Image (tube, rainbow, N blue to C red; front, side, top):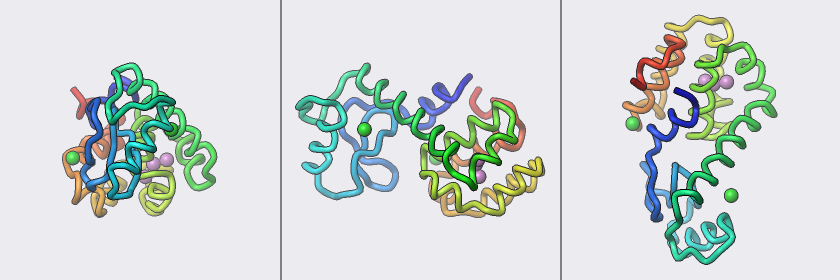
Length: 162
Ligand SMILES: [Cl-]
Ligand SMILES: [Cl-]
Ligand SMILES: [Xe]
Ligand SMILES: [Xe]
Ligand SMILES: [Xe]
């Protein structure tokens, strides 16, 4: 298991524009297109992202391409953030994958706000972090996904994904 397979499982793969759990237009492997309610705005952001007139549909390769870009951006966002990087560098490989998933999902600012959990993770207080991480809107809105990520930070193993 790795970050890619992990996110492919949590996000799924959809070749046509769809709405995510918050109702925003998305495509591929969780590639958010726009927060706007306008489908045309979404079609325009998609065409710009792909480089062609897609008419709201892309191929598997195009999806995987956007996915690679998005994972890369997520890692880079963590490294660039002064509140995230030190935590991230303190973690083992498995746990780092969990941090990437969260950022991919809610953004760097979003994760940078889990101050208290950040500190517990840095201190390697796994069970405590786990409990604090569940006290969030993220967990109440996508509890199955949040449980899998939480267990991963908790245990340092990929068990929740097997
Ligand atoms: Cl893009
Ligand atoms: Cl979920
Ligand atoms: Xe992190
Ligand atoms: Xe994190
Ligand atoms: Xe976190």
